[PDB]
Length: 44
Length: 87
Image 1 (tube, rainbow over the protein chains, first blue to last red):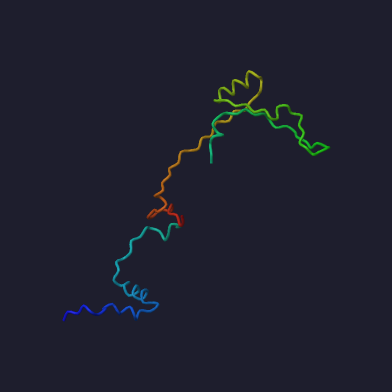
Image 2 (cartoon, helix red, strand yellow):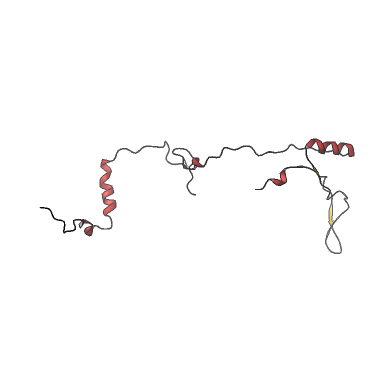
């Protein structure tokens, strides 16, 4: 049924210190290879 | 950084001895030309003045700053070394 009387954004009550970086680590396998500037850094 | 004291030509003479005054320690000189400085618009004017007065002279070419290529955008180069690490 249709309910407009409850808050449905309660998952973040269980988030912790490493939630964001853990999610970032999980996303790594989906990324496309990064482009390259041709050197290790501007100092190479 | 100001460049306004590099507009005109100057004529100066060789530096001679200065010594300490025995009484006060002041800098004494026997050179009457020690403070003499002449201003000229061009090198040619200065050379003509020296020749007619009988002074041997050394002329030195005017040194002009070389034109430079300045680019603010080079500070953030994608792949060059001109990328700055701080602002």
